[PDB]
Amino acid sequence: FNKFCLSLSPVGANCKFDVAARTRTNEQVVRSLYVIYEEGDNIVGVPS
Amino acid sequence: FNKFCLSLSPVGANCKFDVAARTRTNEQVVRSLYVIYEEGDNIVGVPS
């Protein structure tokens, strides 16, 4: 990414993730996490 | 338009505009402005 931010308020958000409580059977959504980003190459995620 | 309204609350909104702070380089969104409208011909925007 060139930019990547997480937010608890949908202002400028580009997309959102669904936060859920996963139990023995059913998985249910409790909150949404907002994501602001710009595709690019300055920032790289890594496994470590 | 037959109808055109601006709102600060997304109830009935048909679409929204993105309000941003444009600086020397980066442009970033601060607020959203909601638009309620019906296509038609009763109301015309004008340059003056």
Image (cartoon, coloured by chain):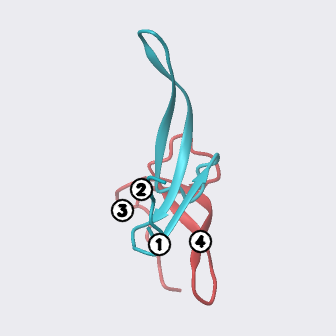
Chain colours: A cyan, B red
- For label 1, the SS is loop
Q: Residue at x 58, y 87 (%)?
A: B25
Chain letter for mark 4 = B
Q: Which residue is mark 3?
A: B41
User: Is B39 displayed left or right of A5 in the figure?
Assistant: left
In primary-sequence order, the first of circles 4 and 3 is 4
Instruction: Tell whether label 2 touches label 1 (CB within 8 Å).
Output: no
- B21 or A46, which is in the foreground? A46
Both labels 2 and 4 in a single chain: yes
Q: CA distance from mark 4 to mark 3?
A: 34 Å
User: What residue is at 34 percent from the left and 58 percent from the top?
Assistant: B40
Identify residue for label 1. A2
Q: Are marks 3 and 2 in contact (CB under 8 Å)?
A: yes
Q: Which chain is home to disc 2?
A: B
Alpha-carbon distance for marks 1 and 2? 42 Å
Instruction: In the rendered structure, find residue B2 and report the number of the disc placed on it.
Output: 2
Q: Amino acid at mark 3?
A: Asp
Crowding at dot 1, Cα within 10 Å, few <14 / some 14-19 / many 20+, comes out as few
Residue A23 picture location, percent across and down? 49, 13
Given residues A44 and B10, the one toward you in this image is A44
